[PDB]
Image (tube, rainbow, N blue to C red; front, side, top):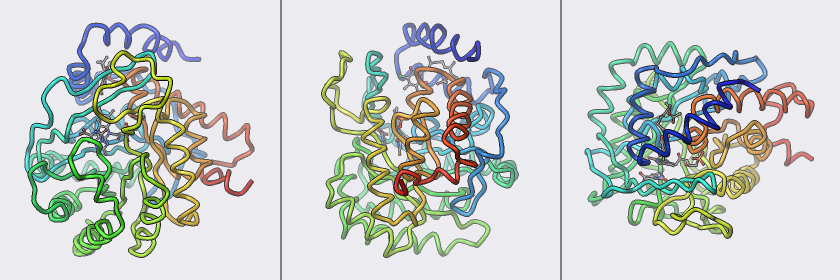
Length: 366
Ligand SMILES: Cc1cc2nc3c(=O)[nH]c(=O)nc-3n(C[C@H](O)[C@H](O)[C@H](O)COP(=O)(O)O)c2cc1C
Ligand SMILES: CC(=O)O[C@@H](C)/C(C)=C/CC/C(C)=C/Cc1c(O)c(Cl)c(C)c(C=O)c1O
Ligand SMILES: O=C(O)c1cc(=O)[nH]c(=O)[nH]1
């Protein structure tokens, strides 16, 4: 049940959201997290939540998705919250402002958010120095089952997308357990076209060459993060390229540019990517498809609308080895992490799984 879950979800978060504009709230959340001003994460991770994937041990399979800690300011606070892994970014090569404010919108009636941040980023150099300041602390955390992902973007005005990603691999690759080639932001003109077969093969060949050129101890896994809005053709092409090139994994999915029938929020027709509950099943179905297309041989990090243990287990059974959440944190606060983990453990036991690993892709074997 938990007292603070109820307190954060029913009282504290909705009260604070009533007082603070969305981006002000985001900024305050990053600040509070970075300072460790967080409730006591009392959930002890059980052995049945441990997952071995991407050349690493993950103490639990619940991560924070990209876009919360864009500039790597709150990594340690996020582990304190009870996340099994942290992904920072997206980070662009040069600093850039992103879109004019306002650029984030709450849809409380839908338990959703729409954002059009447009890759606001401190840039590679700032983030590099921030990560270097805690590099050995991270090495110990990783060893202890708490890996770090770095999500790479491209600048708005760059004339060579592949070179932007290559720069990211060179600069932040040595500080990351895994890198994410984010070709699925809905908020950068032309970006999602990099998901097309020919463009993706060329781009990923260059990214993988740059990764392979790093020293062994500094050589991260490379994942591609994909949209929920892809055609069947697009998904077939991505699966083919992933297998051809030996891409280490997929992150499924980014936000949607669709607006599902039934959205109630006043701000439903704002431009941007939609996240949270209305994305959940679209993301789950995309995980399911990508798992089948890759014959279950390519690790998937499942993301989109995870707010409960059931949501997490649905993505795991569809083929995810790990899951992430973001929007649920914005509505329910830090206790949501312990909630998801406790519920997930209980459901695994109820469905006769020895642990998370046993449940990965279970629906495909029914
Ligand atoms: C405000 C906001 C900013 C985001 N920024 C990024 C980003 O910089 N890079 C990225 O790959 N995904 C970004 N995302 C997408 C999330 O990583 C995630 O894929 C998506 O929100 C679905 O998960 P959720 O429903 O749990 O939020 C962002 C999402 C939100 C809501
Ligand atoms: C769990 C959390 O997000 O932050 C904790 C540390 C907290 C007590 C934050 C206070 C400020 C609030 C109410 C933040 C909620 C919120 C939001 O309301 C919105 Cl709209 C966004 C985009 C974010 C992005 O992180 C967001 O955190
Ligand atoms: O910076 C953003 O606008 C952004 C990037 C991304 O990958 N996904 C998203 O929803 N927003």
